[PDB]
Amino acid sequence: DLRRQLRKAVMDHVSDSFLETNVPLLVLIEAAKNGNEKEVKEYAQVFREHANKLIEVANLACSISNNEEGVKLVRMSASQLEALCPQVINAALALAAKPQSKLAQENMDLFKEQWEKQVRVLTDAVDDITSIDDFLAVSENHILEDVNKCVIALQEKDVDGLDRTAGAIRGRAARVIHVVTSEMDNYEPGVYTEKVLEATKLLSNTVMPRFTEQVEAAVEALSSDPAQPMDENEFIDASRLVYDGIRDIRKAVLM
Ligand SMILES: [Ca+2]
Ligand SMILES: [Cl-]
């Protein structure tokens, strides 16, 4: 529960005052453009200190993440920000000494754009290991689309697409159960945890298994010659249930 508190606290990456590096960078750049070496040097320290704060928040988030793969991207992304920082400062100092230097202007701009992109990659990486909310909203978007492709495949008698779409649904559904289950080991018993876990079990033990059997039966029938008849309604019903199930896990995790 304390780590869960630290997590939310660390959610201060959502534009934090002391973790904010884009504004200090625009200011450092403007001093560079106006050719003010002293101003640059002053703002360079502020920019570097917030980048260091941002990095510190990211490393900390990594220490309370069992997401071994999310954590690697964060660490990698952090180390690249670290290497990039002094190079941005030197492009500013260079421009500060030669403000009319067009090359110094172009380099500043390329470093600025590179910093913005790298800061975005890091913050999204830290968002991923401190909240599965985004993950679930995306998972839900993909499930709906894949379920819809699965039913169109049925209507177009596309056995390949049926098996392929059903494989993507099953794998995404299985990953949702895994990402939610573990995440639940950060809370204590209550009507919350239980509702999330009952939603997850209904998906894995009841919904997924019957969707699988309907896919199997559709393929078996469509692979006939002529196609052997079938109940498209049970198939449609079972595929929709996959979406309902994932959507319910998401609602539960949110409350
Ligand atoms: Ca993201
Ligand atoms: Cl995730």
Image (cartoon, helix red, strand yellow):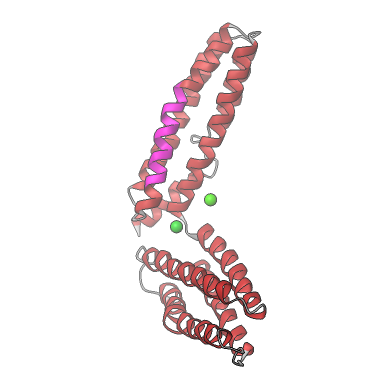
Compared across the picture, whether 3 is left or right of 159 comes to left
Q: Is residue 2 in view?
A: yes
Q: Is residue 94 above or below residue 56?
A: above
Nearest the eye: 150 or 145: 150
Residue 129: x %, y % from top left: 43, 52
- The magenta-colored residue range is 72-86
The x, y position of residue 125, in whole percent, is: 47, 47
Q: Quadrant of the N terminus?
A: bottom left
Say if the magenta span includes residue 51: no
Q: Main secondary structure of the magenta part?
A: helix
Q: Name which quarter of the figure residue 151 lies in.
A: bottom right
Q: Residue furthest front?
A: 225
Residue 70 image point, x, y percent: 40, 51
Name the residue rendered at 42%, 64% in the picture.
Answer: 179
Residue 6 seen from this side: no
| Residue located at (58% from left, 19% from top) | 107
Residue at image coords 54%, 77%: 242
Question: Viewer-proximal residue, 194 or 33?
Answer: 33
The image quadrant of residue 187 is bottom left
Up-down relation of residue 123 to residue 224 (above or below): above
Viewer-proximal residue among 87 and 233? 233
Q: How many marks?
A: 0
Pick whichever, 198 or 224, lies toward us.
224
Residue 219, position as x, y percentages in the image: 54, 82
* Residue at x 47% of width, y 56% of height: 131
In the image, residue 49 sits, relative to residue 19, either above or below, namely above
Answer with the quadrant where ligand 2 appears in the image. Answer: bottom left
